[PDB]
Image: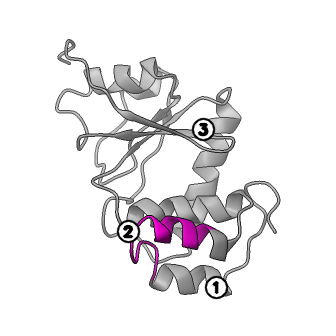
């Protein structure tokens, strides 16, 4: 509860999706924050982070609550995937190609790491995708991530792959 202010988030439109990365680490009022994702046309809360509060406002606003330990920590490369596709599959299956508000720090690792997971499941090649997010950032997804998808197989969650 504070109102006022004019926070300008970041909307990222993909092949057939659209997310909203919060420039700053959540809002100290929430009110203004909810309006930001609500005005941008995003039917999803940037709860994608170290959230620890019950959704009261965004809840009655009919906005999809996206709460995930995407902000440091979180489980290994294999569990989070479930929420990844699920969310991106819900926010879009619940709203008309609306946007998905998610919380993010600076990017790096997670940046390409997370996006990579959804990218591949979207129907993109692991190698190709990697080279992309990798060429735009030395050692972006490299690590357990690369090896993970190397052995991991796409269940065709987000459309058809390969």
Q: Magenta segment, which residues?
A: 129-142
At a point 83% along the width and 59% down the height, the residue shown is 160
Q: Which numbered mark, 3 or 1, is in the foreground of this view?
A: 1
Q: Residues within 10 Å of mark 1 (few under 14, many from 20)?
A: few
Q: Earlier in the sequence, mark 3 or mark 1?
A: 3
Q: Residues within 10 Å of mark 2 (few under 14, many from 20)?
A: some
Image quarter (top left, top right, bottom left or bottom right) of the N terminus: top left
| Rendered location of residue 43, percent (x, y) | 53, 29
| Residue 114 horizontal side relative to residue 49, left or right | right
| Rendered location of residue 3, percent (x, y) | 21, 13
Which circle marks residue 150 in the picture?
1
| Rendered location of residue 124, percent (x, y) | 71, 63
Q: Secondary structure at mark 1?
A: helix
- The residue pinned by badge 2 equals 109
| Rendered location of residue 9, percent (x, y) | 34, 32
Q: Are marks 2 and 3 in contact (CB under 8 Å)?
A: no
């Amino acid at each position: 509860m504070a109102r006022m202010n004019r926070p300008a988030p970041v909307e990222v439109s993909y092949k057939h999706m659209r997310f909203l990365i919060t420039h700053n680490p959540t809002n100290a009022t929430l009110s203004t924050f909810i309006e930001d994702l609500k005005k941008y046309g995003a039917t999803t809360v940037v709860r994608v982070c170290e959230v620890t509060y019950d959704k009261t406002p965004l809840e009655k606003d009919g906005i999809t609550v996206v709460d995930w330990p995407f902000d440091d920590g979180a489980p290994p490369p294999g569990k989070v995937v479930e929420d990844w596709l699920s969310l991106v599959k819900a926010k879009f299956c619940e709203a008309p190609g609306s946007c998905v508000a998610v919380h993010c720090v600076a990017g790096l690792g997670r940046a390409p790491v997370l996006v990579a997971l959804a990218l591949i499941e979207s129907g993109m090649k692991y190698e190709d995708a990697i080279q992309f997010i990798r060429q735009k950032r030395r050692g972006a997804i490299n690590s357990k991530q690369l090896t993970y998808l190397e052995k991991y197989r796409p269940k065709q969650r987000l459309r058809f792959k390969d």
